Image: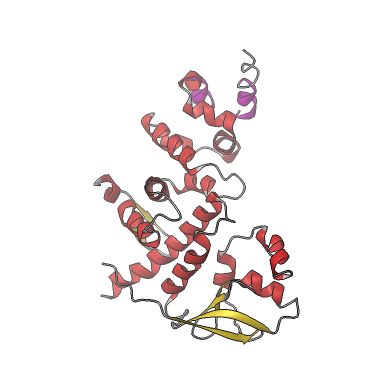
């Protein structure tokens, strides 16, 4: 079901030139702006130690590392975990989530984007175990790029174990997220996307909606020029949501010049 040995770590001070990098760990963390503002503390205050593993591979803090390596620092506070990040990725991933998932300097949509990346990696490493050895939630499935298959219920069971205390996401949010990830990935991409960052809750409203009209695939099989703005902006979003624009909704099943009729009439 779910085995989970306890993580052990020793705190030590290591040479700033000892830590080895792992591309997958450095990319994970979505690039933000805290790289800039953090300098105002690294210049005027080390406080939070890095997070490395047994072979001294860096797991969390690649940014903070880079800055200090340019600030003369020769020593670096790190947390040393007793596991092989290479032979056991899952543990490392869960660490990356631990120290970043609750980090308030990250948007809700920046958390979700990360939460999904991790959830995917984890589901993959897990799927290998099954190969080496309420209802609708288990009816629907999805196939990851590595051939790994999983359903909404199995996937939701994976989110909860990464956030048992809901200290990152609510409960319904995990449900709304597991459903969107398995049933309609293309739609969740708008949610976990820096460019649109459409509210998860709003994407689930569009979900139930287009489903209650029986045009899910029609919406999905649209071109971006049409689908994008329809979901991206409020205007278009209201079409699919407000009965009053139903007639218009099929007329497009544009967008802009439809949105045009959505503004020129908002005068009254």
Q: Quadrant of the C terminus?
A: top right
Left or right? Give the position of 108 relative to 160.
right
Image mark count: 0
Tell me if residue 251 comes above or below residue 128 in the rendering.
above
Q: Nearer the viewer, residue 123 or 7?
A: 7
Residue 34: give x, y in percent of width and height.
66, 60
Q: Is residue 142 above or below residue 122?
A: above
Instruction: Tell which of 255 and 126 is nearer to you.
Output: 126
- Kindly identify the residue that appears in the image at 65 percent across and 18 percent down: 264
- As rendered, which of 226 and 110 lies closer to the eye? 110
Q: Which residue appears farthest toward the front when viewing the image?
A: 45
Q: Residue at point 54% right, 50% down?
A: 109
Q: Main secondary structure of the magenta part?
A: helix
190 to the left or right of 266: left
Residue at x-position 47% and y-position 21%:
246
Residue 88 lies, in percent from the top left, at 42, 78
The front one of 230 and 250 is 230
For the N terminus, which image quadrant? bottom left
Residue at the spot 71% in from the left edge and 81% down from the top edge: 73
**Picture quarter containing residue 165?**
bottom left
As drawn, is 218 to the left or to the right of 41? left
Query: Magenta stretch containing residue 156, yes or no?
Result: no
The quarter of the picture where residue 37 lies is bottom right
Query: Compared to 186, does 119 lie above or below?
Result: below
Judged left or right of residue 52, residue 143 is: left
Q: How is the image coloured?
A: secondary structure
* Residue 195 coordinates in the image, percent (x, y): 62, 47
Q: Which residues are magenta?
A: 247-261
């Amino acid at each position: 079901g779910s085995h989970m040995t306890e993580l052990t770590y020793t705190e030590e001070v290591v040479s700033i030139e000892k830590l080895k990098e792992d591309d997958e760990f450095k990319t994970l963390v979505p690039s933000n702006n805290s790289r800039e503002d953090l300098e105002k503390s690294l210049r005027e205050k080390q406080i939070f130690p890095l997070i490395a593993d047994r072979d001294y591979v860096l797991i969390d803090g690649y940014t903070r590392l880079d800055i200090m390596k340019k600030l003369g620092f020769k020593e670096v506070k790190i947390l040393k975990y007793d596991f092989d990040s290479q032979q056991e990725r899952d543990k490392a991933y869960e660490l990356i989530w631990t120290f970043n998932g609750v980090r308030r300097q990250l948007n809700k949509n920046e958390r979700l984007a990360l939460f999904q990346k991790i959830a995917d990696r984890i589901a993959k490493i897990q799927a290998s175990k099954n190969k080496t050895e309420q209802i609708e939630e288990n009816e629907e499935f999805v196939t990851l790029d590595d051939g790994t298959t999983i359903s909404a219920l199995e996937y939701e069971r994976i989110l909860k174990e990464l956030d048992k205390e809901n200290k990152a996401l609510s409960e319904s949010d995990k449900r709304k997220m597991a459903i969107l990830r398995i049933n309609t990935p293309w739609l969740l991409k708008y949610v976990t996307d820096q460019k649109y960052k459409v509210p998860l809750d709003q994407a689930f409203r569009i979900y139930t909606r287009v489903k209650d009209l029986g045009i899910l695939d029609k919406l999905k099989d649209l071109a971006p020029a049409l689908r994008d703005p329809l979901i991206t902006t409020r205007e278009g979003r209201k079409i699919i949501l407000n009965d009053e624009y139903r007639d218009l909704l099929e007329k497009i099943i544009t967008t802009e010049r439809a949105i045009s009729v959505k503004q020129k009439e908002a005068l009254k």
